[PDB]
Structures are given as C-alpha cells and as structure tokens.
Image (cartoon, coloured by chain):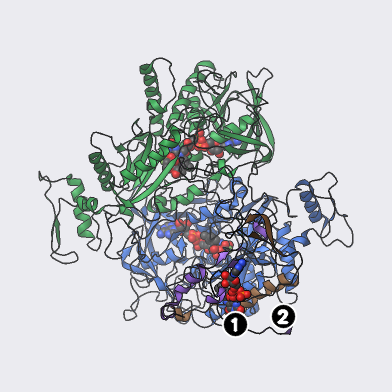
Chain colours: A purple, B brown, C blue, D green
Amino acid sequence: NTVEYQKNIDKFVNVIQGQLMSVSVPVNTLVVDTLSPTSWQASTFFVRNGSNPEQDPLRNLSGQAVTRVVGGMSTHWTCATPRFDREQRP
Amino acid sequence: FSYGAVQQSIDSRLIVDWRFFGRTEPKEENKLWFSDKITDAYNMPQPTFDFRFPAGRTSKEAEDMMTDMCVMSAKIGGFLPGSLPQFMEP
Amino acid sequence: MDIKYDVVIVGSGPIGCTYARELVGAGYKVAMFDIGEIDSGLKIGAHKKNTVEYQKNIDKFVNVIQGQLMSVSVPVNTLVVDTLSPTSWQASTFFVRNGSNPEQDPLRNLSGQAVTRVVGGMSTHWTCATPRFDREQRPLLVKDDADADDAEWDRLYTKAESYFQTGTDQFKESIRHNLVLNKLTEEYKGQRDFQQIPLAATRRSPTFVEWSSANTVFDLQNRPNTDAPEERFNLFPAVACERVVRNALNSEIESLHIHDLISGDRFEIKADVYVLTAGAVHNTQLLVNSGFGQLGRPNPANPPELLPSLGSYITEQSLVFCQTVMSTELIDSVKSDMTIRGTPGELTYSVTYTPGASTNKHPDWWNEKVKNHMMQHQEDPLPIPFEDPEPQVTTLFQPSHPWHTQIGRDAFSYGAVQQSIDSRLIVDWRFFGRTEPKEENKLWFSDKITDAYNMPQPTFDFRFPAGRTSKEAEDMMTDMCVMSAKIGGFLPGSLPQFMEPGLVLHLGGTHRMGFDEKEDNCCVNTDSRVFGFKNLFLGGCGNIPTAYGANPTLTAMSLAIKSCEYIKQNFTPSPF
Amino acid sequence: MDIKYDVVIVGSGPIGCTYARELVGAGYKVAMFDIGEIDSGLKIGAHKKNTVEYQKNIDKFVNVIQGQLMSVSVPVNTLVVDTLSPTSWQASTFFVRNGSNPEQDPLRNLSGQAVTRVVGGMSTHWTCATPRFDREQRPLLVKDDADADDAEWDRLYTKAESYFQTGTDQFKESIRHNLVLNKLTEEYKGQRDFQQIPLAATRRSPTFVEWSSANTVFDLQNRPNTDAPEERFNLFPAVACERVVRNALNSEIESLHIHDLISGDRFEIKADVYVLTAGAVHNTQLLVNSGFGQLGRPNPANPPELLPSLGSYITEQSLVFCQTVMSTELIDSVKSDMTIRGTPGELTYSVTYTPGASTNKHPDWWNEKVKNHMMQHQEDPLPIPFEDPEPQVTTLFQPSHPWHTQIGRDAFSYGAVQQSIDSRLIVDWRFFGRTEPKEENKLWFSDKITDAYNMPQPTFDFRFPAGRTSKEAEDMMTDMCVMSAKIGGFLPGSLPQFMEPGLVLHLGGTHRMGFDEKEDNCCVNTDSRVFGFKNLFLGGCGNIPTAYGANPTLTAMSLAIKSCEYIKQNFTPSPF
Ligand SMILES: *Cc1cc2c(cc1C)Nc1c([nH]c(=O)[nH]c1=O)N2C[C@H](O)[C@H](O)[C@H](O)COP(=O)(O)OP(=O)(O)OC[C@H]1O[C@@H](n2cnc3c(N)ncnc32)[C@H](O)[C@@H]1O
Ligand SMILES: *Cc1cc2c(cc1C)Nc1c([nH]c(=O)[nH]c1=O)N2C[C@H](O)[C@H](O)[C@H](O)COP(=O)(O)OP(=O)(O)OC[C@H]1O[C@@H](n2cnc3c(N)ncnc32)[C@H](O)[C@@H]1O
Ligand SMILES: *Cc1cc2c(cc1C)Nc1c([nH]c(=O)[nH]c1=O)N2C[C@H](O)[C@H](O)[C@H](O)COP(=O)(O)OP(=O)(O)OC[C@H]1O[C@@H](n2cnc3c(N)ncnc32)[C@H](O)[C@@H]1O
Ligand SMILES: OC[C@H]1O[C@H](O)[C@H](F)[C@@H](O)[C@H]1O
Ligand SMILES: OC[C@H]1O[C@H](O)[C@H](F)[C@@H](O)[C@H]1O
C-alpha cells in the first residue's frame, strides 16, 4: 500500500522474498569441484549454513517459510479470501 | 509473488497467471516435529518435516488439476516461455 | 571425373539415393555430387548412431546431431553486453557480425531451420520414423478417383518401405514400450489407436539396432565393382553444385556448374538428365541461382519469368515437446504378477511368478525379465531391466487429432540431460502439427548477402497461419498435456513447450508439386519434372504441397520412385 | 583374422600408430585392435575437423568433441528434484542410477576425465599442440649426463615432430595472431618469450588447415597393398581387448584375450610382442584385469604381486581458462598505417597506405589486407578481415612461470558460444599447471562395479597436492589474469575460472616409467618394457612420471619411438 509499490508492482516480489525464512533446509550436497587448489575444501557434506541435519530432503516441504514481522504474513499476502464449501470445511 | 526473473520482452498487458491449488488428505504419518538437539535462529527446537503428498485421491487430484490448468489456460492464450506449467516447490 | 553422364544427381541424402538406386539399377551411367564429405565410416552415407559406442552411450548422440545442424538464417544479434571492461573494443551499433543475415526479420523466421552437409545428408542422424500420410495430409497423384489414388500411393509407399526397411515390431520386446503402449490403448479405448512408430531400422540384438539411412537405400560405392560389375556410378564428395544452365527455350537443361572444394576449380558437367535432391532449402537456392523464381527480396511488381511459385507456400510444422516421469501406478503394474517374500538384500529374499498362471497379466518373457532383474539387482528399486529399450509409440494423425505423435525417447534432446531421475522412468512426447500452405510464407535468397559457400543467402518470411493452423497447434499442445498425464507428470526442465520454429526440420513446399503450374501454384508435376523442362527433376520434401503433420521423408521417397518410373520410360541409358 | 602375428597393438590412437609406423615399416606382421570403429571418412583415423564444412563453421566442432568424450567415473547423483507431480514414481533414496559409479567419492574425483573410443582415438578431435618438455618437466633417459640426456630427447622429439608434421609458422599470416604475439612480446620485453604454439598441422590454403592425427602418423590401411606391397598390417575395429595372459614365471605374455563386439564372440590372439596403447585409463584397466597391480579398493595390507606402482602417482594438470575482448588500443593499432579520407559508405571514401613507407608499422601484406577489408566492407567497423585466422600463441613453461599457455581460439569451447560480440575480437587463454606425483593419488578399478564394456569400473582418488602444486595453480590463475589484461578485458560469460578436474585430458603417470621398479616406483623401463616381462610394452601418457604442464602427446610419442628401437633390436620379423 505505498504509491511506489503500486507504480512498480513488479518489485514487490522482492519484499515477499525478503521475509520468507525457510522452515527446514536439508544438508546441501552440491559438488563444487572448480575451487582453486589453495582454497579450503570440504571432505564431507557437513552441516553448513544453518541447514537442518534431521531433515530428509526427499520428504520435506522445502518451500515452507515463516515471516517474523508485526502483522505476520498479512503484511505481504495476496488477500484472497474465499469461503470453503461443505466439502472442504470442518 | 512471481517465481522467476520477470519477462520484459512480452507486453505485461498480455500476461495472465494461473495458480490451481489442490486439497490434501490428512494423514497421521505426515508430520511436523521438532528436534531435541538441533535449534533454530531463536534457540528453539528446530522444525523438521516428514511429508509426502498422499497416494490415492490427493495424488490423482493433483495431476488432474495440472491437466485442468493446461486445458483451461489454453482458452485464453498459449503458455509464456519461462513460465511453463509446473508444480511448485512443496 | 568424366565430361558426360547419363544422369547427374545433386545431393546424397536418402532422396538422391532413391534416384541412384533406381537409375543405377536400370543401367544408367550416374554421377552424384555432394557438397559435403564422407565421414560415416566405411559404409558410405550410413547412420552415425550405428556404432557400438553410441548405442552404449546414447545420451551422447545429441552432440553428433548438433554438430551437423548449421542454421539457415540467423538474424542480426541485438543482445546488450554492458559489462565489458572499459578498455575493450565496444560496438556503437548492432552491426552485422558472426555470419548473421541482415535481410532476416527475427520475428518472421524459422530460427531453428538448419542444414546438414555431409554424404548421406540428414539421414546420417535422423530418427528413422517413416509413417505414411493418410488422404487428408497427402497430395493427389490421381484426380477424381480416390480408390485409384489410394492404390497408387500404396504401391509407392510399399516400395519405399522396402528401400528403407521400415518395420513396426523392432521394439516389441521392450517392457517400457509395451507399458506405455498398453496404457494408452486402454485409456483411449474406442477413440484412438496406438501402435509402434514405423521405423526404418533392423534390430540386430536386444541391445543393438541397425538404424537405416541413405546407405540402406543405396550403398554409395563406386561402380562397376565386383558385386555390381555392369553398373556405373560415381560419387563426388566436396563438390558444391552452383547452377543449372537453361537453354534459350527454357525447355532443357544443358549443364551443371560445379565448384570442387578441394582444388578450388570450377567445372561443368553434362548429362542427359539432371536431378536436384539438395534438400528443401538448397534445391530452391540452386534453382534461384539458375534463373528460376525471383532472386532477392520479393517484389510482386516484377513478376518472375519462370516458376513463380518457387519458394512460396512453404510449410513447416509446429512442434510441441515435453517429458514425463513414469507414474507409480504404472511402475507397480510392471511387477503385478510377482510374489515377493522377504526383504531385498537378504538371503531369504524371493521374487517368484508362475509361468502360465491364468491370472498373470503379462507374458512369461516379461515376468522372467522382471524376476531376474529384481533378484539379480536387489539394490535397485525399479522392476524394469537396465537395458530395456525405450518406448517407440504413436497414435497416427486422424481428422479428430490432426497431428502426428512420437512417444518414447528421441536421441535429439533439447536441454542438458537429467541425471537425477532414473532414465527408465522418462518418456518424451513430440506432437507435430500440419501447416496450411500460404503464398505469403516464403523462402527467398538475397541478391547481396551470401552464405558460407558464396551462394545467395537464404532468408525466411514465415508466420504460422492464422486460422486452422494456429487453432490446431494450440489444441495439439493441450492434447499432449492431456495424453502425457495418463503416463506420468512432467519432468522438471522438460515442461510442455513449443519448439523453435523449424527445429523440427520438416520443411515442405519450397518447390511444390501439382497437376497444373498455374492452377495448382506449383513447380513440378506428378513425375517431379519441372514444368517446361524435358530433363530436370526435383526430389525431396520441397515437393510436398499439402499441410502434413507426419514425418515427410517416406512420402518424398515415394514421389522419387514415381519420378524414376518416368525417367526409365523416357530416357535410354548409354551403352556400357 | 589370423591365429598368430609378430606384433599386436591395442589401440589406434596416435601412440598405437607410432608403434605401427615403426614396426610395419621394419617388416613385422602387425595386427592392431581398437574397441571403437572407423568413423572419420576414407582416411582412417584422421582429424574430424578436416572437412570444408567444419572449417567454414568451426563453432560447431565443440559438438563433435563432446559427442566422443565419455566420462570415466560419475558419482552417484544427489540432486533434489521435489517438483515432480504427486503421481510420478519418486525415489526414497539416492540410489545408483544412470551408469553412476557408487565407488567414487564425488569430492576426490577427476570429474572431467573422459575417454574416446573411435579409430584414431583422441587424435580425431584434439587441438594438435605439440610442445617439447624442457628439462624441468621431463623424465631422464640418461642418468648423470644432462647433455647426453638432452641429445637423446632432441633426437626422439625431432623424429616425433616429423611423424606429426609439427610446425611453428602455419599462422604467420594472421593479423590477429600477430597482433597478440607482438603485444605480448613487447609487454614482457626481456622477461618472457612468445611464439606460435607448435602445431601438428599443415596449412593447405588461407582458409584451410590439414590438422594432424593418428592417420598422419600411420594411414591405417591394411597391408600389403599397392603402395606397400611387402608390408603386413591389419586393423580390427570394434574389438574390445580384455586381458593379457601371463605365463607362470611372470616373464612373458602368452596371448591377448579379445571380444569381437559385432559377433559377440571371444577369441585369443597370439603374438611375439604385445603393445598396449589404449590410453592412460584403459591401459591401466587392461593390466589390472590381467593380474597386474591390485583390483578393487586399495588395500595397503594386501600388497600387489606385480607392478605395485600401477595406478598410483597419477597426475592430472590444473587448467585455468578465460576469454577476452580485444582492447580498443589494439584494434586501432591494426590500422595505424592507413590514411582515411571521407565517411564510410560515401563515394569519396578513401583508405590508403604507402607500400614501403619507412614510417609504416606493418608489412605491406598486412596493410593490403586491412585497406581492402576497409574499402570493400565499409559497413563493418573493424579493420580485421573476415577470414583472418585465429591467434595460436604461447609462452612455454619456464622455472619463473611453471605453466604452459595457449592463447587464441580453441575449438573446445566450454559454454554456449557468444554471438553478441564480434568473433574477431575474442581471444581464449588456457594455462596448464604441473602436478606433483604422489602415491596417494590413484586410479583403481572396482571388483564389483563394471563399465559399459563389462570391464572393472574405473574410480579416481585424487586431490591436487598441497604444497607446490597448489601454490603454483593459484599463481597460474593470477598470471592469466595479469597477462590477459594486456590484450583486453574478460568476456562476460568466460570469466577466469578453474576447469573441472580432468577436463584438460592430460592424465599421466598411471603406468609410469623409470630406471628401477622399486627405487623409482614405476611400471616400465626407459624402453617402455614392463618390468620382468620380455615382450610386453606400454605406450602413452601413462608412461610419463614427472610433473608436466605442456601437452604430453609428443613426449609420449618420443618414448614410443625409443620403445620401438628396442623392439627392432630384440625381435626378428617373421618371413613374409
Ligand atoms: C506470504 C504469503 C502468504 C499468503 C499469501 C501469499 C503470500 C506470498 N496469500 C494469501 C494467503 N492466505 C490467504 O488466505 N489468502 C491469500 O491470498 N497467505 C497466507 C496468510 O498470509 C496466512 O495464512 C496468515 O497470515 C496466517 O495468519 P496468522 O495465523 O495470524 O499467522 P502469521 O504467520 O501471519 O502471524 C504469526 C505471527 O506470529 C509471530 N511469531 C511467530 N512465532 C512467535 C513466537 N514464538 N513468539 C512471538 N511471536 C511469534 C510472527 O512474527 C507473526 O507475525
Ligand atoms: C536432422 C534430423 C532430421 C530428421 C530427423 C531428426 C533429425 C534431428 N528425424 C526424421 C526425419 N525425417 C523423417 O521422415 N523422419 C524422422 O524420424 N528427419 C528429416 C530427414 O532427415 C530429411 O527429411 C531427409 O534426410 C531429407 O532427404 P533429402 O531430400 O535427401 O535431403 P538431405 O538434406 O538429407 O540431403 C541433401 C544433401 O544435399 C547436399 N547438398 C546440399 N546443397 C548442395 C549443393 N549445392 N551441391 C551439392 N550438394 C548439396 C547435402 O550436403 C546433403 O547431403
Ligand atoms: C579430446 C582432446 C584431447 C586432446 C586435445 C584436446 C581435446 C579436446 N588437445 C591436445 C591433446 N594432446 C596434446 O598433446 N595436445 C593437444 O593439443 N589432447 C590429448 C591427446 O588427444 C591424447 O594425449 C592422445 O590422443 C593420446 O594418444 P594415445 O595414447 O594413443 O591414446 P588415445 O586415447 O588417443 O587412443 C587409445 C585408443 O585405444 C582404444 N581403446 C581403449 N581401450 C581399449 C580396449 N580395451 N581395447 C581396444 N582398444 C581400446 C580407444 O578406442 C582409442 O582409440
Ligand atoms: O526435434 C526434431 C526432430 O524430432 C523428432 O526426432 C522427429 F522424428 C524428427 O522427424 C525431427 O522433427
Ligand atoms: O580443454 C581441454 C583441452 O584444452 C586445449 O585444447 C588443450 F590443447 C588440450 O590439450 C586440452 O587440454
């Protein structure tokens, strides 16, 4: 709800991304084998960069994230508010 | 909440997005749990997921849902290269 | 090299080779020239995928295809690179760089169109799918008599299928192939028919297929030789054919002008009969360089003298593509006859079936393969044997689904190939649309710009026609989405998409056939003879004047067979 | 195929072919087997880049290279794909998929190592750089007499250069080549020397180079033939050589076991002399499959019986790469002798020079080329002619810069090629480091896992050594940054980087040479004879036991020449 974001709405994705903090990131196993020989080089895929060694990467909700700001996720959300029909509703 | 570098090539007036959202059967085995050793950024038990989309109706519906988006979106225009039909990160 | 031949053939692709097979066989003294060189091994013009190594590493063959597809027309590049160092030489304009074609509008191109200049042409790398066209896609050879027209095509297609060794059962023993084929049959029960793609190929073993090519049609060995002591054939590679010379009457060709690329020398060659099978693009180039049609940017106020339809009414097919990952239901079905006891990896583990058990869903051969894989590779989570061949499935074009389809695993992959997902789970989907011929869709050649061989540069002016062509193309995409979903979800990175215009390499109608030059807007008659000329014949997919979706080569060959009938009936071979 | 030959050679690459040239020539009855097939045209084993089409489209040749580099050892993939549809079959583990090697640690691999199985081996696609090694990079052939050692290498290298037709002036008439060469000479005045890369090649015209290959060394035609009526040679492609058979003494080989890949049959072949030139990887594979060294994961507590250094002390070079965009100063220098009057595109426009003018910075030939380009292409903003050949520049390895360098434009590009920036402005930079031999750096072969030819799967255990190897590699990167800057800024998308370990394909020391098996930790003597064996010889870069930075093939050939001296002095050819 700023005049600037509604004149440049293509930029708002960046606001959303900057307050979605991933819930559970598995241990990374990407091979980087083009480091210079002088650089410190891992022998294992050890727990690095806030990854969660408990998480199976194949049984995750990798895209799950949280927002810690006053107003929560409603400071960035799409504002769609449908009712549930009987079939979806407790 | 765009999911890729946004297109500049094609006029924005021509672009329409399609998001279809499936329902997921509740199953006991699909879990959110918290580590007794690992902690998050606020020194609280680290969240860990053990999740797969259920077999059966959840999965059949999800794939029928993809097909439905293909069929319906075609009534309005062809896919935008770089935003082809896809499932998003769980 | 002689002065004088009975017949000269320009190009050694499978269509050139149809002409050689027929005319060498009928006793003519034949010379064939190709701009490209012999580079397929000792079998000249053969398929490059017929090595033991490529069939053990088929994922690498895409690189062979890419290394001999040379783009037809590349527009001027306008990409901004603004991170050069300040010291580097930096353009002020987007000037004509790197062999781009300044005549080409980037928005009306067939960017994916490419050519192959090697002995055997494109048949040294092609997929080998050879469907017949049904009536709806096919030009008439007989007017006003459909059963007679049908009979003639059946005669010609039967012969063409023998020359190519087309068959429909080389993949019958593949689990994956049958898995897919049977699922689709069952889902479209009473609506559509599925079968193996007709493939020009002979299986040599469970792990090796001898894919057909130009060599299969005609082995391209110089004659006479021991096997053919009364035949006369010479193949001259690395010779660029530049021009056919018209007499003043425009009733006969008098010579073929050639440039020997090794010596640099230019010559002329005399023959009774001239046959141009240089490809849909390069036939048209040679003709335009010879005074047929119009050179340069089209100018409707300056009408061409000869063959005014040349280069117009061009067609190229729309192509949609995706891959899928086999469904869990389908995979579990492969092993539905197995009784499993114990835990894989253990001494007690047992996978069994009964050979003949009435309630078995699969043949014993299939259950044997599955049992053995599962017991011999108890670390592998899939029931499909490692060397199981790929599916080769189609539902052929029909009025209700007016596209051709090829479902399986094509060597010509379009992205870095996936290593993450097991290859046994992957199935490719290609659906091919038909394109209405329209006068305004053109291939033309620059009067100023030249290509790598110093010939007039090819330029496209093409858009998919509005109307049925476009409606069908988009219905075709939807159809692939709907059908592919019956087998499994899309493979991330191979999502449904249209391919670059012309990547498909099914260009037609650049020198099209018809009964009457004026009424049918065409260049050659149903014997493939150029109107007005006694002794000039065109062969190839440029001859096809209709909107077709199936792969055109078998059709083009069938037309060349008919052309060769005319030649044999109208020209006498020299004495030996 | 006969029962019995004088000499059998395993592999048809340029090292196999050195053995054939020497021994066929000396009158031996020779059989040569290759696992791969003839696929280079009628000149068997020749360079695939010697077609008119590839030299008109050299940007496409990378695809030919890629299509015959088959990775040696691919670790198990662990990429997460979590956007599959819920219906697709989805793995629970990262299981052994798609021909990966479960023995391979992904963090101690030569991931870029690959092999080529075609007649002529890697010499059908290689760059053709053939530098000599200076003393610092080179194994001793004479102990305790440096001038004598120098003399012997010079004798052998001179011969090897003739077999390959090495020269240093094929690019002397290139503006770009000279532009670069001269600038570097001037900037490192009195510090370093620059020259043309020595290249195994003969220029045939201003636009065509006949690149050397195995065919150049030996034409690979079966003999006797008309040209060589008293020679005896047979080449058997599509034959996998599996094992050499040792006698019980471990003093002689008694047969070579082979698998004919077309028939599927296995045979044995008897010869007086056995030569293995299968490549640095596959020589070691064949040996290990024959009871030399140790099969399986290394086990220092179970010492091998024979050749305990086999597969250890392996070396592979570090490789750094970038491209640049020619500086504005350099480009303007090309045309510094021209007087320009008027505006390009106009009737008055004039570019002139004086042919001999004392103050001219360039030779008349150069100024003629530049004047003509500028007047004939007044729409082009550059002074460099379109068909100007690429630079081919080096400063060879010296103690003060202990790397080899190649500056110009290599066919083996490493990314989608740029179309945006004019190709005339682009120069590539490759700097090649030397790697200390260390016992712990290993190539070994699985006792369980097999490759595509049912042979023990190759597995690497490699890291660049700490110490000098690593310090030098990083100084080498810095050196490329510093030197390349003298010519122009980096090309976006080709920024300075180390390449994937082993992409360089300069693997050495897998069956290394020395004077004494124990003291020098080696497998073959300075005649390339396997210790203890009367009639088994190894050829190839696996023989090289030192840390070298220059391209190894000419060195390996020089060693094979010396090996063939021994063979000629110690074995009598059968009667004809
Ligand atoms: C991010 C996002 C979210 C939604 C949409 C799209 C985008 C990209 N679109 C959308 C949504 N929902 C709809 O119904 N329709 C739409 O079109 N989005 C989801 C929606 O945004 C959420 O469902 C909604 O906010 C949930 O409300 P809530 O239950 O109030 O929860 P919040 O996460 O918003 O706020 C919680 C709040 O608590 C704080 N916090 C977290 N942990 C603690 C602890 N330990 N102590 C104290 N406070 C805590 C957070 O900081 C947060 O502010
Ligand atoms: C590349 C490709 C092509 C096909 C398939 C897939 C791939 C990736 N798959 C395929 C095809 N067609 C089918 O029916 N089904 C399949 O599954 N492909 C198309 C097919 O490959 C072509 O339709 C067929 O070869 C055409 O045959 P042709 O008319 O004989 O033409 P070619 O292009 O093969 O050969 C022409 C020949 O002429 C030479 N040439 C060109 N210009 C000149 C000049 N001026 N002088 C002398 N010679 C010339 C070429 O060098 C070439 O060899
Ligand atoms: C691919 C590559 C290679 C080189 C350059 C660049 C490119 C991209 N550039 C280059 C090289 N070397 C130089 O000195 N300077 C250059 O500028 N390249 C390396 C060079 O290409 C190799 O060093 C050289 O060929 C090695 O020669 P060789 O020892 O003869 O080995 P090859 O690998 O060429 O040939 C071996 C041969 O044996 C066959 N084979 C393999 N295993 C078997 C079995 N079991 N039985 C039978 N035959 C077997 C292969 O098929 C192969 O043909
Ligand atoms: O990708 C282009 C190719 O796709 C498939 O292999 C077809 F069979 C070919 O005919 C060609 O269209
Ligand atoms: O990229 C790998 C290649 O780079 C260059 O062409 C070298 F000359 C080759 O020897 C090889 O190392």
Circle 2 SS class: helix
Q: Say which mark, if any, is on residue A88.
A: 2
Foreground of the two, C230 or B27: B27
Identify whether C102 is placed above or below D359: below
Could you say which quadrant of the image residue D460 lies in?
top right
Q: Position of residue D427 (x, y in %)?
A: 33, 49
The reply to whether discs 1 and 2 touch (Cβ–Cβ < 8 Å) is no
Rendered residue at 63%/23% (across/down) = D306
- Residue D75 visible somewhere in the drawing: yes
Residue that lies at the very extreme toward the top in this rendered image: D144
Q: Position of residue D129 (x, y in %)?
A: 39, 38
Q: Amino acid at mark 2?
A: Gln
Q: Position of residue D429 (x, y in %)?
A: 36, 45
Q: Which residue is mark 1?
A: C144
Q: Amino acid at mark 1?
A: Asp
Q: Say which mark, if any, is on residue C247.
A: none
Identify whether D208 is placed above or below D6: below
